[PDB]
Length: 76
Ligand SMILES: [Zn+2]
Image (cartoon, rainbow, N blue to C red):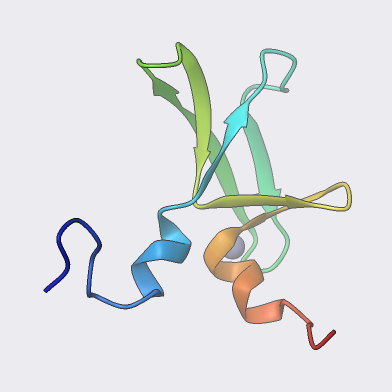
């Protein structure tokens, strides 16, 4: 019984991630090569900017956070 944290495991917390879409972006979109699916930006009224929901950037490539989490090679 958390005060403000969810007890529903880390499974939801991967999908809750986002990254800000710049005004220089090509139509606010990119494609996930893992599942072959296109992400689109969504407006944020507080900052006055846009955000890519469930999205991650790494080494010049774009992916879904839930997709890339399955392929994250790590040990060091
Ligand atoms: Zn994907």
